Image 1: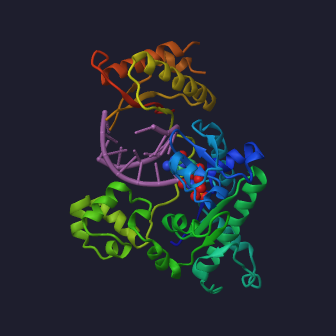
Image 2: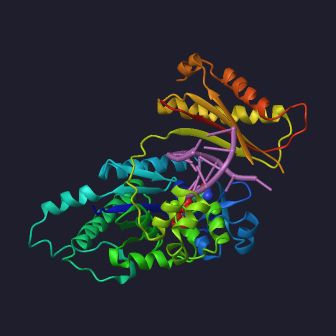
Image 3: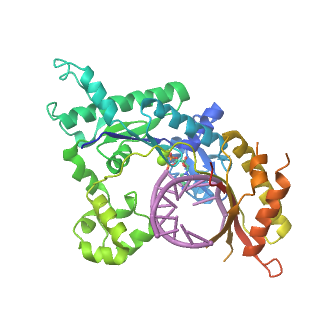
Amino acid sequence: SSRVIVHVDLDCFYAQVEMISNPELKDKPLGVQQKYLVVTCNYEARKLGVKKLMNVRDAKEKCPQLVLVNGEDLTRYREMSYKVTELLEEFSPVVERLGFDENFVDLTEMVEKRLQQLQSDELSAVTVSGHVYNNQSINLLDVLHIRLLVGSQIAAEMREAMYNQLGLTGCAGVASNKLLAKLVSGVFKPNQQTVLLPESCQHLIHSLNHIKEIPGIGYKTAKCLEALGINSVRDLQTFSPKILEKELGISVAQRIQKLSFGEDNSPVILSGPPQSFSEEDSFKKCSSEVEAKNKIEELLASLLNRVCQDGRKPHTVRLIIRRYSGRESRQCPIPSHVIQKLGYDVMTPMVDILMKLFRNMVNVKMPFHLTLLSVCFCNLK
DNA sequence: TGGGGTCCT
DNA sequence: AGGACCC
Ligand SMILES: Nc1ccn([C@H]2C[C@H](O)[C@@H](COP(=O)(O)NP(=O)(O)OP(=O)(O)O)O2)c(=O)n1
Ligand SMILES: [Mg+2]
Ligand SMILES: [Mg+2]
């Protein structure tokens, strides 16, 4: 009933890919920029005071010698991401994707198959690969410790394979569930791995300063818990279950309370092929229908390129826009003939479709100014 | 004024 | 169609 789970997080992913593209940026402090924001930066820049998700002004101010690379086109990063996911799928068929650079792999069955091959005299030769959380002493007779050590061996093999086959470095965390693996992956960064033995579990769960640092607790839930006087992990462990159920609903309360103890009963789910494609474009303002129509033709073009390559045809189109000052969206199924024609000029009809979806949301007669325009193809089959 | 994704309601 | 979460 006890598992072995590994979590893989790539170091400065966008920056890493940009460095692989042209090695001219290997030692220069590098930051990947999308509009007025630096999503990530090279670790050389991270030394200079540059942080992830800084303003471009705050980045160049704290580090003027910073070199910036535009990263609004995610195509190369996406290619690398799925190469990583496939590589990990080689080890175990079930690999769950989180983000572009995070991956969960269930090593349990693989670890057992490994253990049955070893002999009684060899069970003493098992050694850890990478870091052990909190320098915890290993009990070679504790079977859980052994299985987690094998998990660290498989994790090291995974990272070595990633570097030799894709030229990518990453951090890994081996634990007994998903939450603890993802939490223990980032203990030693960059390009280091850490295994967490059960005794140290509580320590890790209290190393956190605030509760938002837990996956599954976002801005809304954390704001509500701040309003409820919950500011620490122990504050959530000790909170009355009934009151929390009443304030957050039944499901969320049970789940985040179980998370508050580091308990994760979730299994690794084979992510497989993506359930949707989408292209985004933001700006300061857009106040012309023809202005919006051209951007929709652009996003529509890139999406048309992407859908014909997957071989899976989308069955529903969605338009999302954000007005100036929240998001709003209107979708509809794609007609039968244009679905079949994908793979014939399919450009002209789709536009009209989206434009209809556009005119429903915004009255062209009344003035308007749009902040965000995004197109999505979903319901792939 | 980031550019994507997931599932639940 | 919107809302919560993740990177
Ligand atoms: N809000 C976000 C978060 C991440 N990303 C992209 C940029 C990152 O290169 C990539 C991975 O994000 P991340 O793992 O949170 N931090 P990154 O991998 O850049 O460096 P580490 O801090 O993991 O070493 O996703 C984004 O575009 N918008
Ligand atoms: Mg990450
Ligand atoms: Mg990362």
